[PDB]
Image 1: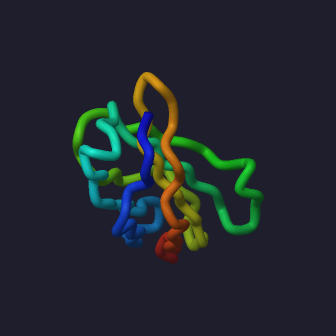
Image 2 (image 1 turned 90 degrees about the horizontal axis):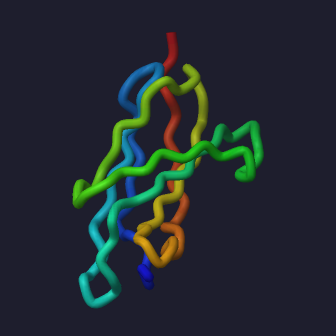
Image 3 (image 1 turned 180 degrees about the vertical axis):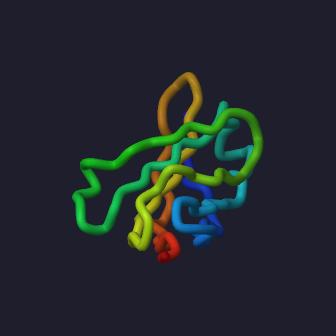
Length: 99
């Protein structure tokens, strides 16, 4: 079971519909993930409406696509493996571009 959240989490605006989320891998002494789950939600909606994307393997970023334009998004990232989900990262935010 992953025991720690990823660190150095950053969200970066890419375009009207894309945001890059990147993080640092967890120390192996804290567990070995099958991947990470990124939860994301629009600011004007609850965290309980969050959509999720899973990565698989050891890449420490994902470019989220199909996002609403000119919109503040919030993100958290957590590791996962067969035994379950690890704790979530600090929340980060970025806004998709305008017009």
